[PDB]
Image 1 (cartoon, each protein chain N blue to C red):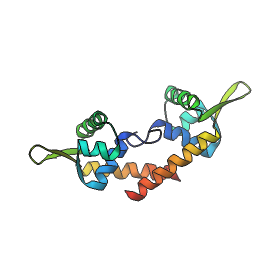
Image 2: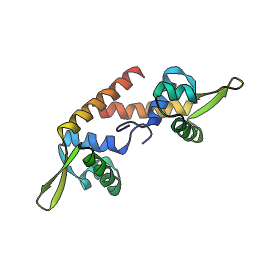
Image 3: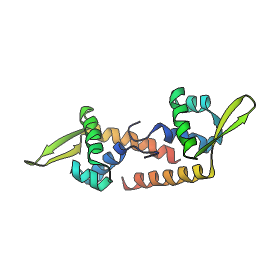
Image 4: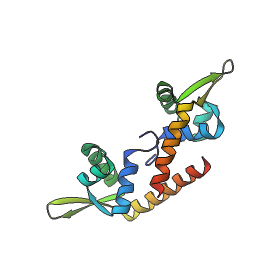
Length: 84
Length: 82
């Protein structure tokens, strides 16, 4: 995690997948379970992510504010690649 | 600093300017001085960066493994944008 934080991976995973459980995010991003949960709390607190209960499970998905933040962040990264 | 770490902007700056002092890095990246120092120390410990002083001033520059690290990292961000 030199350049990127675990939140970057968590957010980017939700972009292409849409909705995902904490366990699922953890496995696909190879970020420990507890770490994912901790980061999800921050994302929820900031209004970037929202919970969606499907039966006895808890899924997560980006909000409109979360999708604009991801897009804006990815575009700034792309510019960093250009300049560098 | 949601996606990128301050350590990322510090490394990118050195990649663009070649060498710079802690104060120069701080003002060009808008990162607090102490935070720059804390990240610079980590970079020195990992051998990713080395200092070069011209008397009183102390500049920092990427080493070879430091540049290989940046290349690897640049590939990661590149891949995320996809």
